[PDB]
Every structure is written in structure tokens, then in C-alpha cells.
Length: 44
Length: 49
Length: 111
Length: 120
View 1 (cartoon, chains in turn red, green, blue, yellow):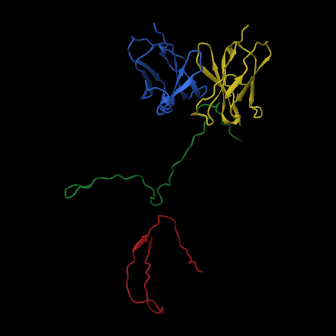
View 2 (spheres, helix red, strand yellow):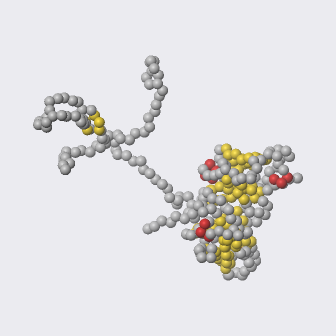
View 3 (tube, chains in turn brown, yellow, green, blue):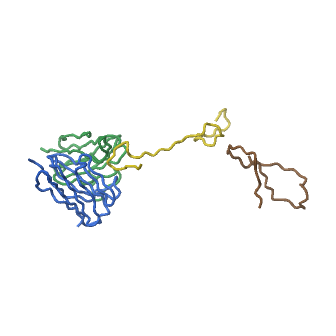
């Protein structure tokens, strides 16, 4: 399950994480059935 | 070894096309299912459709 | 000689002529039926093919129908020149060999 | 003219062989399959052999291992050799043709037919 929230709105300096709240709609479900314990991110 | 497919050979020697609709032994979540039926709509009645 | 065909046909004058062609489901039920008219001493000629399309220039006096695993040819208003030979052609599968086995031959007599 | 010409069977002697030449005219040889038809007196039609315009061939189940039959795409002619004659040869033979796709096809060309008679 991939509970996703793509928010194209912020106007503020980066600093630390902001103060706020918002839910996360469910978008992506895969019945892949495999077991994963290890992962990496795709750095450029 | 090779084949021998000629019109001389009768029934039982012509090639037969075979497809096997096997499945996993119900271990992973179900991802394929058959067709589902349908029923007309009834408004304001003690019906369980 | 698996196929069975009448040796001859008889009937009173002024009656419609009906010829039944019955076989199996492999050659008629599962395959198209070819209807040939053969003249005495002449090679057979294809007249009816596919039961849906007909060659141009053929009058519609003859009629053909298919029911179940059999077919019937109906001719209305028999004339003296209708005495000829008629052949059923279909693809059959035999134990010895599978192919296009035709009929034996039907002979008509007019008194 | 569009015609398939085949020479009739002549008289012969025991221990000899009969050669029949079938030639197609009026159309290209590599356009229609070549088919054999047999008709006995007072009997329907029987078929023996198949020769493709360019490819293999199908022999006769009953007349196998003793009939020479091949193809030659040079003169648009084919030759059939018969040996070990028998009284069963008394019939009329059609060296006919069919459509270019076999199975569901029209038998547009017909042959005159060769009368073969073997007797003692």
C-alpha cells in the first residue's frame, strides 16, 4: 500500500518541517505478494 | 528428432493446440476472478438486491 | 460406403421433389456443404456453395435448407429435363484416411 | 487455352511401366494445386494423390511404394509412372486442379480424363 499525498503548495523558507496537519488519501494498492526488508532511494 | 506433418496422416496425428490454465495453490492474494452478475434496481421496497 | 443414398426416387406427377442429404456432424454440422449437379457422361460441376452465396445466373426455382445435421433439397414444378445426377460434397475424417469423399450416384426414372 | 492435358493409358505388357504426362496450359503452374481423381464405371469419384505447385506431395495410401510421382517447375509438366499392373486399373482418371489455398476451394479446372483398362 502506498498512501500518498502530493501537495503542490508551500511558500516559506526551507528551514525545518512546518507546523500543520493534513490527512493522506489512499491511492496505490498492489497485490505483489513478495516480502521486502531492504531498500534504497534513487539518488541523481 | 523432427516432425512429419502430411495430409496422409489421419485423425490423431494433426497438431493440437493446448493451453493450461493452471494457478498457484491459493497462497498469494486473489488477483483474477470470473464474471459477476447484475440485477435491476428497486426503490423503496423490502428487497435485498 | 459409410454414406447412405437412395437408389432412386419415385412419386406422382405434379408433386414437389424432396431429396434428403444426411451424414454426420463432422462434415455437415461442423463443415460447409457443397451441392453439385452432374450431367450423364459429364464431369461434376459446383452449383451450391456455403448455403449463403450463390453464383449469378442461377434461377431460384431450386431451394435448399439445412436442419440439424441434415439438409433437404426441394424442387417445385418438376419437368422432364430435371432427370440428372446430384452429388453431396463435404470434408470427412475416416479411420483409413481423412479427405473429400463424395457420393455414389442417384439415378431418376420418368415413365 | 486454360486446359490440363493428360495422355491416356495405352496397351502394354506385364513387367513394364506406364508413363502419364499431365501438363497445365493457359495459366501459371505455380498458381493451383494438382489433384488426382478416379472414377470406376458405375461408381462415384475417388482421389489418389496431391502435388503442390511448389513443395512436397501426398501419395496414395492404397497405391504407395509402387507409383512414381514428382513435380518439375520448368515445363509446367508432371510425370506419373505406374508399375505392377492389375485389373483394378479399369477406370477414368482426372488430373484436375483446385484453388491456391486448398481446403475450402473451387475446382475451376477439369481434365478430359484418361481411360485405363487392364485385362488378360
